[PDB]
Length: 132
Length: 132
Image (cartoon, each protein chain N blue to C red):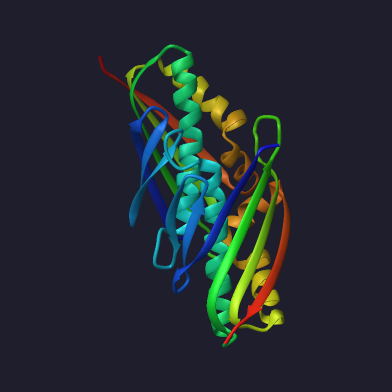
């Protein structure tokens, strides 16, 4: 069971210098938004799975763009009632390969998404931009 | 229902330039770790609540340090089976104030934590370092 550790300390009012094993960022009221960072966590987690699965399936990836949109509820805790995630793969990629990669990532591999799925409605879509 | 939107694009192999409304960071295999970013999201989300509640309770905050440790399970999806969060408030802060702030944040206010609680075991502790 691998262990992940991060440490935060105030850098300014309600704002934290956040230290991870390989880099620091500023998050809080006067830094990056915590809920936006959650979408970044989800997106990169899944994006990494997708990139690896596509390469394993021997597809030629020129780029992968991921768009995430979270709709927050009105009452506290203001969680995302739903998150829309759109994956776009550019290069020589079969749409069925992208489909399998996205399904494996969202249903099995991406850990961040697995942790939030029970609390939100996910709306996933994908498409390929064929290019030599 | 406020909406949060982020956009990711490859910056290198399995690594994404991640754009939020107010800043960009690099996440993925050759960037910040997605699961570590999740802990940062949780920590800053909660930390912001704590800072605001303490100020509202008229406490004198010199600093707030937050330590997060996530123990990942062995099987896919490798989610955090548990997350330990330790809050340390420095300055003129009553321990009961910190206690209420932490409980309100973890049970009501922090949205990120609310989304993951159903999937993990949280172990929360707090302490005050009294200082003039």
